[PDB]
Amino acid sequence: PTSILDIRQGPKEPFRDYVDRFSKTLRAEQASQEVKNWMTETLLVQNANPDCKTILKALGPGATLEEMMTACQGVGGPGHKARV
Amino acid sequence: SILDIRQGPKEPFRDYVDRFSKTLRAEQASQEVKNWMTETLLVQNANPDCKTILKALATLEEMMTACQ
Image 1 (cartoon, rainbow over the protein chains, first blue to last red):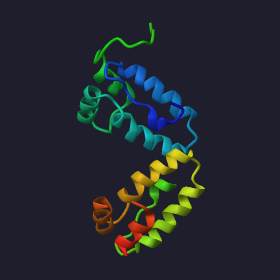
Image 2: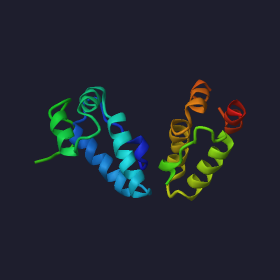
Image 3: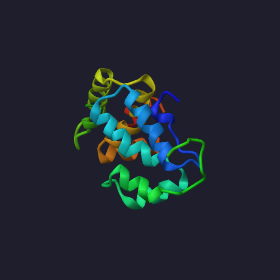
């Protein structure tokens, strides 16, 4: 989990599934808008799995969520969340 | 905002801690997030001299005695 601090990417978890869990927990999290933006720029890359973290760090902080997801697409296993 | 609380180059650590504590208590966040903010932002936003001491270090009283 009910805390944004506990949202961590699984070793085989697709980045899109991790982002969805992070987004849902952050929206429910009680914090100011600037703190939520800071939580995204800190915790999202920090709590990503080793493979995605390596990609995201090379990409830099000055990149959008769509650019992050495109760079991490297909990395890892299939996961357990059904999507179209 | 707690994010903007930064120690001055000549500002005593005790004065910085007082400003950090007052802003954190007024900040709207969960108890675990506030504890995490203390563990990350307090040392991170301290001046170069205090930051060097704090990284080598613990309770707040031990931090203030080491930075006095």
